[PDB]
Length: 314
Image (cartoon, rainbow, N blue to C red; front, side, top):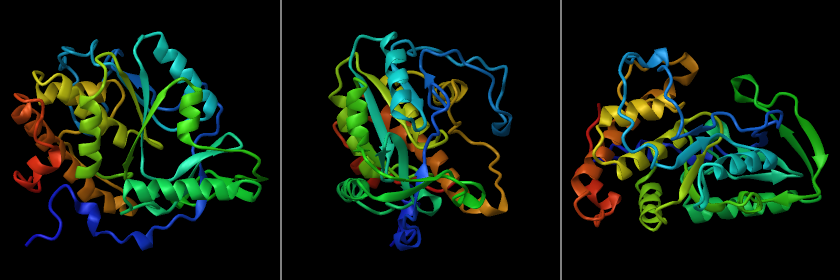
């Protein structure tokens, strides 16, 4: 009897130790676009040094022009509009805003905020149904009430900010639709590998897409969740390209590197170590899943294949 298999490490943490306590400012709106905006039509750049990769290696670009995917971090309503217009110049198919955030978020007087708990784990352990209902209630309850909105400083605690009585409340779904994009939510936890549930939901969604759909993924700040799904899509659609090529190319357009590398962390972030290792193992397992189920149309869901082919720690 193993209590939590590789791939499900985060199930051992206690949700009650990370409840939300403040409305975090997700973007201050000074720039025209969200941070980390990147496309599969982009030129590859030099790898980041911390990953210790071969800068002379030239990754295969086979399948990229036809991939049609992009990524970024959180945005204001006007920033989303700029992303949607930019993506329209590249395609005539439907454009999707794929919201990968498990944490409750929305817009207060047009300001993008999220209910933030330590490690950004305020909805840890909740089903997607429970996570979205917490979100709808918190947002509605803010209307006509005084609130404190603030950016996180060091030690990940509030620093400065503003206080206003709220006169308008909006959902991410409402904001995407107003920008001309279709909406699809996948409640993935910040900092850890997506659950078998998050992935089964993404696979079913993928199988039903029109051949010219363009997928725009987004997380809160950084590139963690967004690169995981961008890598999975590249593999699913281009099963003939090697693991090394897929990993190098998703990193060189501006994403994270999901292959092996020398993991190092500050003392305050040592809790992240085991999660970085689990990710490396799990993306290799997914590539094994794609290669082995490619023949059919992936008749076997990921969760089922996984329970009969468990991964082992690094």
